[PDB]
Image (cartoon, helix red, strand yellow):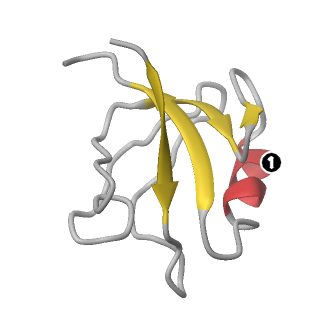
Amino acid sequence: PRVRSVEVARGRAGYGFTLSGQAPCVLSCVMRGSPADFVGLRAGDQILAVNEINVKKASHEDVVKLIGKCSGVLHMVIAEGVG
């Protein structure tokens, strides 16, 4: 039970998973088969850092902006709560 990082390889139209965290950035769910699942993403992992910058209570648009700026791959630091 600790914090880790995941490297997602953005394809062409994004990745496939879903993001929803007005305040507490969290991966609502992932689509098995996308570059996100290829690393080992599992819905529930709370997003702490996005693009090397923390986002405990950041803005949804700002967080998305960072992910849509990867230009090939994004570095997200999430923590597994259950399991």
Quarter of the figure that contains the C terminus: top left
Side of 3 relative to 30 (left or right): right
Q: Residue 30, relative to residue 58: is it above or below?
A: below
Three-letter code for the amino acid on which mark 1 is drawn: Asp
Q: Nearer the viewer, residue 47 or 73?
A: 73
On screen, residue 83 above or below 49: above
Q: Position of residue 23 (x, y in %)?
A: 66, 26
Q: Is residue 19 above or below residue 14?
A: above
Q: Residue at x 45, y 71 (%)?
A: 15
Q: Nearer the viewer, residue 54 or 17?
A: 54
Q: Give the total number of marks visible in the rendering.
A: 1
Q: Residue extending furthest top?
A: 1
Residue at screen point 57% across, 36% down: 21
**Residue under the image location 77 percent in, 31 percent down:** 58
Residue bearing mark 1: 62
Instruction: Indicate the quadrant where residue 18 lies.
Output: bottom left
